[PDB]
Amino acid sequence: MIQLMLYSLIITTSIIFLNMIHPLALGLTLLIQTIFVCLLTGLMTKSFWYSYILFLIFLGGMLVLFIYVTSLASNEMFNLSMKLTLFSSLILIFMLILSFIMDKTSSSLFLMNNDMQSIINMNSYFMENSLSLNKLYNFPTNFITILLMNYLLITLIVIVKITKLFK
Amino acid sequence: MFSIIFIALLILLITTIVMFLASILSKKALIDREKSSPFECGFDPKSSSRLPFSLRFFLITIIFLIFDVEIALILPMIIIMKYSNIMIWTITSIIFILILLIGLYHEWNQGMLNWSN
Amino acid sequence: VITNNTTLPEESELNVQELNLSSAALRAGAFHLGKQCEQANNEFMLCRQELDDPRACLAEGKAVTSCALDFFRKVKKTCHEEFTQYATCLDKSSGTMAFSHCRKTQGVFDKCIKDN
Amino acid sequence: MFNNSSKILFITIMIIGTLITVTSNSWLGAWMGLEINLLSFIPLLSDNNNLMSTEASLKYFLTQVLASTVLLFSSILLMLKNNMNNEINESFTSMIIMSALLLKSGAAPFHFWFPNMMEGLTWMNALMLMTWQKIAPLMLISYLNIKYLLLISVILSVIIGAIGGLNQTSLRKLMAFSSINHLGWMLSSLMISESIWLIYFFFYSFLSFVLTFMFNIFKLFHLNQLFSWFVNSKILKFTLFMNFLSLGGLPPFLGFLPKWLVIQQLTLCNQYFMLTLMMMSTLITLFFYLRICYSAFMMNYFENNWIMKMNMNSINYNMYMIMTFFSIFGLFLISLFYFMF
Amino acid sequence: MIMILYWSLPMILFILGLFCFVSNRKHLLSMLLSLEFIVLMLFFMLFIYLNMLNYESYFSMMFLTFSVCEGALGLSILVSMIRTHGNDYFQSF
Amino acid sequence: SLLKRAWNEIPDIVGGSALALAGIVMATIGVANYYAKDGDNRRYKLGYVVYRHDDPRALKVRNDED
Amino acid sequence: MFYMEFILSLIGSLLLIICVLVSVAFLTLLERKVLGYIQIRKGPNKVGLMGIPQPFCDAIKLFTKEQTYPLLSNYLSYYISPIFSLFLSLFVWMCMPFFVKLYSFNLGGLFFLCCTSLGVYTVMVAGWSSNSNYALLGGLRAVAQTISYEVSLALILLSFIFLIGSYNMIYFFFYQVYMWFLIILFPMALVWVSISLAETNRTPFDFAEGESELVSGFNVEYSSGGFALIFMAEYASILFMSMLFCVIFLGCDVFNLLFYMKLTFISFVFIWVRGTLPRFRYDKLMYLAWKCFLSFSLNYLLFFIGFKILLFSLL
Amino acid sequence: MWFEILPGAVIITTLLSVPIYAMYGLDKLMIGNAFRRNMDERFSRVMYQRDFRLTDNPYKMNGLDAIPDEKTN
Amino acid sequence: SLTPFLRLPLTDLTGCLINHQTYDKCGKFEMKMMECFEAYGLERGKRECADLISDFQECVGMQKQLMRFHAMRNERYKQWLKGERKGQEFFADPPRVDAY
């Protein structure tokens, strides 16, 4: 089933992550991890709003730095090993068959997706992000957003102070 | 979602099958020492050719991240505008954009893209 | 959370008739049903709003479903073809079930109600 | 505010970030403030003019970042399994939060980064890390209430904190070891009470502030430099250097006033054994300070020849030796302090 | 056990991240990438908690905004460091 | 001088800037118009709002048309 | 019933995939013909009957052509990027709006931002796999172009998003039910053409693949089958943007042939630019991205936010 | 002459017109209606549950005849 | 919530940072608690909020309730493993989807 399969894929990729040493191979590994984690948090959330968000910030923009500066390339390309792939396939499958075996429900989270809320709940019949993101802007908990944007402004003042060492 | 997930898996599988198929459809040739060299307009490639990483492109992409995150902050304004208190939503959003402009215009007078190098 | 000391209703108390109607069925007869029976609903889910314990609201809930049942039995007797057509539009016409695509049938169904 | 105008900016952002922590209501808010501190401080520490500054930067960042990572993580666990910021009791949920904070402030077993730092840091940059980058993690340690971990920290907060100081010849590393020992006193003091801890840190801030602020003035970086630093009379060479003994807090130097306060309240808690150990090590702290003061107690040494005059900033020198004079005759102000009751 | 069935996977990944953070790597890039994986896991623990909470959910942005800044600072000091020494290689340390 | 100088150098920014000033002014006009009608006893309410008779909200419910 | 729902959802996805692929492969001819008449040429009219099967002919050539794989061990990594790019260019379609429910896909605008973002990784790793400084410069220039424009692309979206009052794309139809939306946001249309043109890397913003400056940019070290996939991926991209231009500005009338007339005209317009404009410089484009578009988008954001506040005031 | 271009554009616009009419035809034939009930909102979903549970096929809507025929009293 | 020592004007940003109470069933329990914490401080209150902390924790934490289920279903499986439950009896009837 999707949820625990997604655990399994994250476990397998994590084992891949701790083995790989080529920087691209690691950075590639992060990329897959991010899709998986976005999928997983989405499932247990009220909706996928935050998943789309952190996708485009974390992965879409910010992993570009990591791959780009890790374009050192090692001066040479991968020597891919079909063995860790086969073990990855092998470990995936019997984890997957166990996933078919494991208890259908109890092996699932308990969080309350929009569907898993009760019918009577008059609040749930609004736009899915309306009531969640309300107090990010409504007082008196919105000034912290102002702190975020100025933090980012200051972050740029810092980057031009570190990235401007005589060139 | 998983309807989307399955469709993407199906497409990707069909995609790799097509490229896998073309890999057998295309005739093979005995490999050649020179057929597998980097293309440098027909004159021998130099030493490793790994480009220098002393440059600005990370700096531009860092500007991307700052504005990319700031974009994240302002995305939800569409929905909350019907619910949030109007003063706070009004002023709060307005100062976001205002600070952005002032950062931009202050930064033009800085002119940071017109680097000496 | 519930325990054997707690109080619950009787099976018979719960066993009352329900609508069995489709989405298009209800959403078609919505408006002319809303004003006929709103006191039922109003006091019904008012007590639900203020007080959440459903054990007491069972009586008024039975009233609500009965009142709606009564209206549609009147619809069944009086205007069948008009109402059914309006229902058939309201679903066949769109996957969002919006009133803004078969108002002509909505008008004629209103005519029949105006006559009855 | 060392060279550029941006020094003022990052200091300001740093202050706000750390002030968030001390005023933070929930662990998450405190974590938020801590990271803002992490931002604001790296550029000051990572001067672009030299090299050594930059290496200190990776180590500081690469350490603090992990500290914040673990801190927030352990916060979630505590504030999951207890579903409340103030757990009913201190369990394994909470020791990790201290271990985060202890590393962040550079406490006993988690200190090795801290000496390696000093090589890179210049004086006031070091100073600023010495004083202010230890407030927030300590004030949080206040909220955490695991006796035994603090106790092991206090035990080991002087042993290494003094034994290493015996060995160092670079003033940068000595200040590191000097503070780790003093940090031993704060940690014990915070296990006892907070008002006294507040006082003791302040006097430590004052004392460390004046100390390194003259070392910045004359740019004395090595014991040889201290022996060689020209002074017209070789008397103010000695009057100024009393403060090196105010480090040990020997009664007529005003460092005694805080150490007395901590000792009084600590023994009132009846942890007599702990006092003995810290106070045994205090002598080793004062030991290498005399090792420093061989330069000035005796007079008229052998000196270099080329120097004829010695000069320094008006502002720094004018501020500096007002702070010194207080370090000389501070006690008689016994009345002026009313925060001990 | 609640944690063993629910908060276990986040633990196992988080610890594995730290060990890779203290392993042996030619340069520090593998380290930065290691802590970056940890951030994703850090987000994972954070979100499942914020999901316990009806609307406190929005705190994701606060954590995300801060976390990316750490990475940017991380790349900042590294890239300036290659430029200084012509390399930021652990042999230089 | 500066007036034509900018309007000759950076026409898009001048045009954009005039747009921004236009928007904020009418935005303030929007807020003012909003609170002329008190803007909070809104005509149409999300969910199913009900009030017992005499409730201060009930005393306030708009009896208008839309 | 329920499984009726799922079966159809998969049929529609599959059916759309074959159509969009065959369309773009067949569309390539329309570029070759149309550009042929912009220039005073006659364009392909040789094969088949009036060069109709020209693009099928092209595919047969490529798949027959061998795969001159680069240096020994790169086989996979060089064979990955074309897959991972054509995949995005297709799968981005599934969010496109229908009245006839294909999906209930909300946050469609976000998903647009995400897919349009992921193009950077494909091009960059493609150049990296190639391992040829020509290919590498192309990737970097390609990366910089795409990444820079996304900033403006996001804020531009928000203007429309506010003007429609949700992230669900479908509401573009309801709000355009009376009068088209180009005639309201004319300057945005020109900017949006440029943004879309930058994303698909066509000219005047042709730095990524380009010619006469880089041999083919990242594409230079690509053999047949990989090249065919990249080339198809780009044209699936150029069509999709043409669709998005149509659904935003020009009616969103999915169940009206005139919408498909509009698709062709816009995709034609892309070519109409291809044969007219010259190319930009690196720096001049970055000025145009940050110093011109970002300012532009922010003003309209601050303009329309007030307008909708005033609109909300009125009702 | 310019009909030369029409073959292409006519073909492309035709191919892109297909899928919707494919969706419509397959729906109105193979479900009973041309439109699949959109499920973006909580209320639409629960109504979909209500329909899907009253009969296996929501699209096989139950008219007013589903009401009990009569009550004796 | 752990008490900021200084309580300066910049507790005013993060104190209401993220609140349990609003639109939460547990929020009612939070108020039942947090009033007492205000009454008895943070140390005597932590002593004398036995029921308040128990239920407040239980509502959000779901520890007691959820673990009751886990043992409850394990025990169903355990009898199946002993063979008491066969292909039919192994599960109960399905709640009507329109419930809960």
Image (spheres, coloured by chain):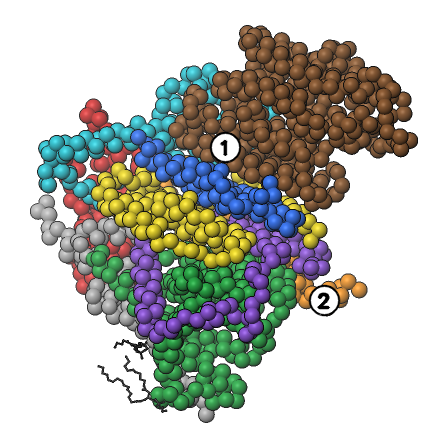
Chain colours: A yellow, B purple, C red, D brown, E blue, F orange, G green, I cyan
Query: Percent x, y for residue D282?
Result: 65, 15
Quarter of the image where one finds residue G63? bottom left
Asked if residue E32 lies left or right of residue E15, the reply is: right
- Residue D157 is tagged as none
**Of all residues shown, which one is farthest toward the front?**
B33
In front: label 2 or label 1: 1
Q: Residue at x 63, y 30 (%)?
A: D115
User: Looking at the image, can residue E58 be seen?
Assistant: no
Asked if residue D281 lies left or right of residue G199, the reply is: right
**Amino acid type shown at disc 1:** Leu
The residue carrying pointer 2 sits among few (fewer than 14), some (14 to 19) or many (20 or more) residues within 10 Å by Cα, namely: few
Q: Residue at x 35, y 25 (%)?
A: I55
Q: Mark 2, chain letter?
A: F
Which residue in the protein does label 1 denote?
A: D71
Helix, strand or loop for disc 1: helix
**Of all residues shown, which one is farthest toward the right?**
D308
Asked if residue E28 lies left or right of residue F7, the reply is: left
- How far apart are the alpha carbons under marks 2 and 1? 52 Å
Return the residue nearer the eye: C20 or C64.
C20
- Residue F9 is tagged as 2
Return the residue nearer the eye: F34 or B104.
B104
